[PDB]
Structure formats: structure tokens, C-alpha cells
Length: 35
Image 1 (cartoon, rainbow, N blue to C red):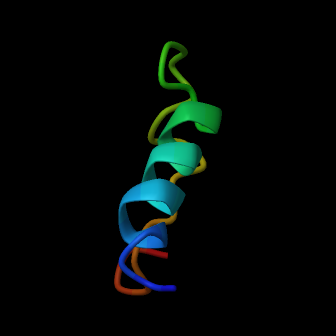
Image 2: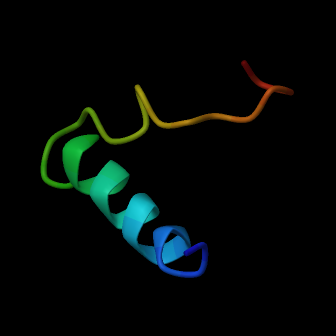
Image 3: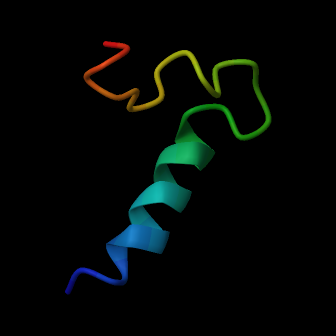
């Protein structure tokens, strides 16, 4: 159980992050270098 989340977790995160709203990119799991 790892190769599923890689495409499932990212899909569930982008859909709830604002897949249709401007939120997409505001709460995104940015890297430590930027966060």
C-alpha cells in the first residue's frame, strides 16, 4: 500500500485544494525549501 496513495493521495489533495477554485496552490503541500 504505497503506489496507490502516490496517485490517490495527490488526486484527493488536488481535488480538495481547489481543483476548480483558486485555492489550488495556496494550501498545497509545498516543500520545506519554500515552506
